[PDB]
Length: 106
Image 1 (cartoon, rainbow, N blue to C red):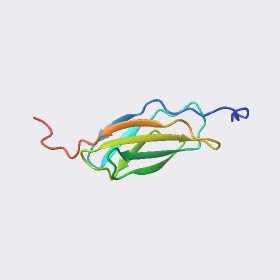
Image 2: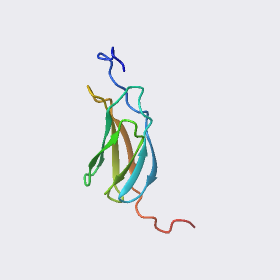
Image 3: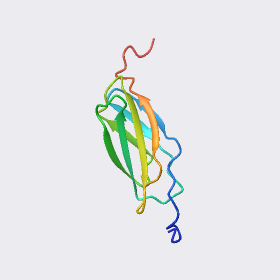
Image 4: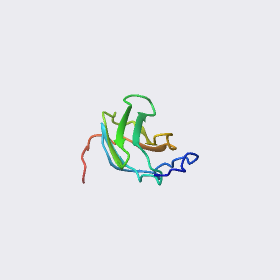
């Protein structure tokens, strides 16, 4: 719908929450926009550079499991709500990879 949504700019998902953090894997969950969007791009990159990836999720997706990260590294997960005409503002949620559970639990 939104026939008169030509001048309408799509909104982004409110700051998504990372559910799980590991060495080479981090999971993030976003609350999709009021805008009708076509899909999602997801660019997660290390602040010190390293393994970066862009995933493509369905318009109605709300979580990406990022894979092939590097342990002990800062990771910017950037979510992109994409619509036919335009791309909404980016989600930037940065999580440092804690790594493989070492002595997890006293």
